[PDB]
Amino acid sequence: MAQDALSDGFVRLCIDPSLNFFGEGCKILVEGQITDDATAAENVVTCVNSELDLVERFGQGSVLTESLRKVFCMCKSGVSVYALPRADAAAAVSAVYTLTVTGTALTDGRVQLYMGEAEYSLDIGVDEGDTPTQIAAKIVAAISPDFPYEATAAAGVITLTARNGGTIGNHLSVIYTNLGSCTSVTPEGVTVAFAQTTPGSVNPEPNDYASVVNECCFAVYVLSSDDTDWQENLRDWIRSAWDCSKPQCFGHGYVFNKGTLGQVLADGDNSAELSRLALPTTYPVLPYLTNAAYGALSACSTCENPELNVQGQTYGLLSCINMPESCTPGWEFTEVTQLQNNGFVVSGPATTSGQGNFTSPYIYNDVTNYLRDEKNRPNATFRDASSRRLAAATGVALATFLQQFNGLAVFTKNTNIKTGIIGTNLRLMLGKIRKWASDNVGVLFSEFDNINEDIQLVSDFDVQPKCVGQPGVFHLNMRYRPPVRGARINVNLVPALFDN
Amino acid sequence: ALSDGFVRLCIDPSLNFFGEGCKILVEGQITDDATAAENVVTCVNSELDLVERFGQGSVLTESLRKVFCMCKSGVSVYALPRADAAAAVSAVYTLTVTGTALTDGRVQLYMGEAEYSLDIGVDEGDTPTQIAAKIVAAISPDFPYEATAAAGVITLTARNGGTIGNHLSVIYTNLGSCTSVTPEGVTVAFAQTTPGSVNPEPNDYASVVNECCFAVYVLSSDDTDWQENLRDWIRSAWDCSKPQCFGHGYVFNKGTLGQVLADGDNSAELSRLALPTTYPVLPYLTNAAYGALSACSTCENPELNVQGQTYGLLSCINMPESCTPGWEFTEVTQLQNNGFVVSGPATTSGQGNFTSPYIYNDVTNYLRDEKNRPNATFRDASSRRLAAATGVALATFLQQFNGLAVFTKNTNIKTGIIGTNLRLMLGKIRKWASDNVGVLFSEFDNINEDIQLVSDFDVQPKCVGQPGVFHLNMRYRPPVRGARINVNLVPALFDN
Amino acid sequence: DNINEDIQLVSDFDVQPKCVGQPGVFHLNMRYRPPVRGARINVNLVPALFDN
Amino acid sequence: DNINEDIQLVSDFDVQPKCVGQPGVFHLNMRYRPPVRGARINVNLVPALFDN
Amino acid sequence: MAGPCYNPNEHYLPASFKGVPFDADSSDSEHGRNGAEAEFVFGERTGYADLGIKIRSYSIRARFQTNDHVALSNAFIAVLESTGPGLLVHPTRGPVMAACRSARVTDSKVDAAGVTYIDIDFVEANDTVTGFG
Amino acid sequence: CNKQNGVKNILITFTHCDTGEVIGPISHEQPDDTLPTYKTCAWTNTALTNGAVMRSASNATMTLPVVRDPRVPLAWYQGCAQIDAQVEKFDGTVMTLTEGAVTEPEESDGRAVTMTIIAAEIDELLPPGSLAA
């Protein structure tokens, strides 16, 4: 019985805020390092539900945990996250960083440091003068527990060592924000110096993608390493998903490269699957944090409709990443032009100022590393990232449409179908396909230059020689162009004045 | 009606009380002399029947007394008496009087709650410690503690066993310049000698409250295990395996900050009330007042929030002002952020004068989710009430499709037929949902996607579905309780 | 579902063998489905909140 | 109660069997109710005490 | 009125005067309160003083269509002219005591033959003792 | 067949005002080749000078020509009963009206009725894939 309204049994009520009306969105796969305390098995793809499940399942302050934190922060809803935790190499060497404090406090003030990312920055205020360097180094009490580095807290100097061995932890940066004091009162006679003493040496090179990701269609692949060999292995796997030997499993991957303009340009490999993000040697943010945020944004959170570019200050803003303002762009405009013309992604701060506040970078151009066609002839067919997404959608949509010809009577020698039969022939099939291509104009295609020559259909017998072709096998050829959209406007403003 | 004075109209009254749509259940201990049968739910009439039906000074009577005094009319009360454990020990307190009253004066004490206060006059000067301690003859009968009046010292023993008798802090006037003609030379000492031992753990909720709907559950105990059982029962009332009865429970937790935070089991079915270690009022009395006030005596409107100094004023409770806030502000914020309820004085003073408490935030103990994500879907208690109201109201609206011809696989309805199809049914439901904006829902983010109707034939595979069964999927959002508007002041000293 | 197969009419002669059928006797077969009416509605209510 | 059913008119040809009725004879059936002269109403007091 | 379920016969009382029924066709009233507004000289502030209630007044219009309207109309006028005030059942204001102050009877023989209109102007009249306090 | 402009189902539910009777959602058919017309914005704009406008209350209106059902009195179809209508076009659009009232009925010969309805608001259900919320 219970309440009278629901007693008669005509209505069954269920109240649960965890139910999901819609099907799972696109899948995004994140890959990186972990620590010993992590309970997750190595080389096993696993699902993720909430932020709190991290740490316990992927260790404290590991590379993988930080990457996932940003991904969850950027994608509020409409995506399913998966993780592929790898492990450190046996002979890994952990990077070591030293931060020294000199002098002695003599006036009251505050000191605040920026450690990698805003979420890890700390503010500590020296309460009184006459405090030596040892009363300082109270920072160790303020360093976030989730920081990827360990605070030694030695006598007057603090040593920072990465929690994950290898070259991954070789990109930290610390800045004395309050040096150019404007409003905050920095203590007088206090200075901070940051330097490195030992770099990482060994990185893992897994090559078991064909076994752990065997025949499952992911949308985006995100890698959290700078090893070129590791990145090359990922690229080869993605190609296998776009190959013609077996059914396709289209996907796309994101990686980053850091160094001088000479070194970064040398990493290009004419890859049509990787979207390489280029960063300068003086990037304040940890590299692998920006990579995940960009890839996460490009996931179904903004690519449920495949035709949407990720650019501009509106659709390409990484609001989850904050870095201090600065007067120096990092990339000189001439360098930016060279990088863009060579299939590299570039990012810049939303606002420029010297006050030293926080801002979020945004993507300048969404581009893939496709530069040269096969047979070494340049073009820009796959320059835009959206082109790859459109190609995958175009193939699937065409395949679904062609399913109607499965198990249909066909006539090839004599083309006259007797009354009452259900069938078709070459010309009628070609006519039907042509109608579909014209109908989709403005949705998946731009107007065909000459549709009569851009589509052809030939039976197997006509191609193969005598007594070699099989019945009921057809060959279809097609050429198509993705839609055009505004890209740039050149303005030549010519002022003039009245005649005195 | 039928009477001698025949006239065109006849009339027929039956009884006074009519508000039987609201129910409240109070659970607690009793004493030996109570005539009520144990573990049997019984309706409770006005205060006249008390004492006899539930014993003198029993925990249940005190809780019921506050419930009736807060909700004069408009709600229906119920009681579920429970008996003490097999080997329950009774707490003992000592109050020793020393010195000889060498001046005329009066002595007054405050214990437990304002209703039990006493005020007697010292017989005369030079009355020794033994003629004094006449306080025993003055203590009101309803006090849950028994006074023995030994030679020079008075002993207070709890009338109910278990841990429920481990809460007291006395306030007196027998020293200092507070000369309410105070008798000079008299002093009093307060100390405890024996704590409570054993509490009951009933687990037969499925048998004594079976298939009976209650609105608010009130529990006058502080045993964590006992409270946990009540939470489990409430879940069953909100379960999906049978018709629901709905409901909400009220409990309290007392101790230091470290202890109180350790009781956060993340239950959306309970509203845990946090109190400090030196609360000058017996705990369960305050909890009963909060439950009764929110026990639909004011919450006939689910939307209403029991907060503030106007709606969340526990008038019946009177307590002297404390010398320190008790809950430091740095601690008040933590308790609120952790899903607890915090109460404090409704007036400003530090004199030791009399005030009343009110409730800051009406919030349940909900945190995280089934999938372990954090959200505030069931943060405010009003959400639980609104969710229940929507379920009942929605079921009534859909009743009109019971026994109505439904057409599928051919949507053209012949002329003169009385029926409907999926699209028409969905359109009618959308009309109802929109009209309720501002009463049960806020404006939907996308009304075209948060409502879906699909026939069972489109869910089950071929030749497996049933004829005339639909699945309705709906998502809603309760009204909006405020928003933040950051301001940016600018004096603009320059002109134009 | 298919009215062309749910109704049939056959004369007696076609059913019985020779010299056994009788004039003016017919066999009629028919299958039908009674009307359908609403029987049960399952509701999956999913509350949410307007954050902050 | 239902004016469409409480009045009926039938010619005698529709009541008697074939070739037994008479021409120009009718049967009228009517059912009526005298005016109502009473009503019973039951009341409740419900003296409230809460503010709202 | 909103909704199509209104029923005018259920919300408007049947008019009357001194016990004689008549068919009402309109219903007005006038209320108010006597003030003492005052504005000083060279001043930017004004004042007010409530100084009693204002006497009400009701106006009604009646129509006679039934056969032989002249007899009923000509017989109702003999009631409005009766000495003293009497009970009036206002269609919307309920039963009140009033005294007729004027009445214009309109009629025609060629323009409108068969219907008589009569406008009325009532005034509230409360009985008072004769000893002036 | 989504490009066909036409009406598919018409459901009405009367509610007698003087007896509280309710009749289930009977189906109807239209008398001729005309189609119903709708107005769902309850505000009217008047043209001022230099591009301005003025807003007026107005209502939501409907026009439903339907063949009378031979089992319902003709009076109900005119302004002697509440109406609750639903019209389903071929493309998929469904538009519902509740608590409507008929205004200014005209004479009908007994088969064709052209009701004019007014209500507080009309709810439109666009086919799948709408843009606006």
Image: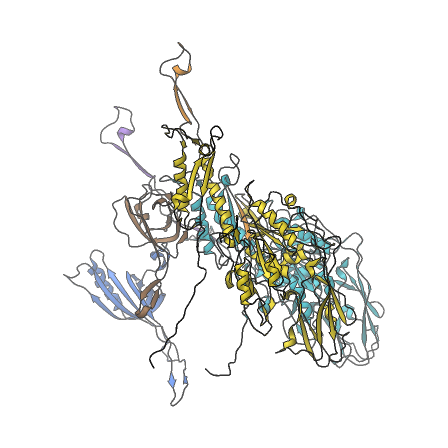
Chain colours: A yellow, B cyan, C orange, D purple, E blue, F brown
Q: Quadrant of residue E74?
A: bottom left
Please provide percent x and percent y for residue A492: 41, 68
Q: Nearer the viewer, residue D17 or B232?
A: B232
**Which residue is pictured at 51% across the width and 35% down the height?**
B462
**Which residue is pictured at 34% across the width and 46% down the height?**
F5
Q: Residue furthest front?
A: A376
Taking B409 as reference, is A165 above or below it? below
Please provide percent x and percent y for residue A405: 45, 35
Task: From the viewer's perspective, tell me whether residue B418 is left or right of residue D9.
Answer: right
Please provide percent x and percent y for residue C31: 44, 27
Instruction: Quadrant for the N terminus of chain E, please.
Output: bottom left
Instruction: Quadrant for the C terminus of chain E, please.
Output: bottom left
Would residue D18 be visible to someone looking at this image? yes
Please provide percent x and percent y for residue A52: 66, 56
Task: From the viewer's perspective, tell me whether residue A43 is left or right of residue F120.
Answer: right
Q: How many marks?
A: 0
Task: From the viewer's perspective, tell me whether residue B202 is left or right of residue B7.
Answer: right
Q: Residue furthest right?
A: B151
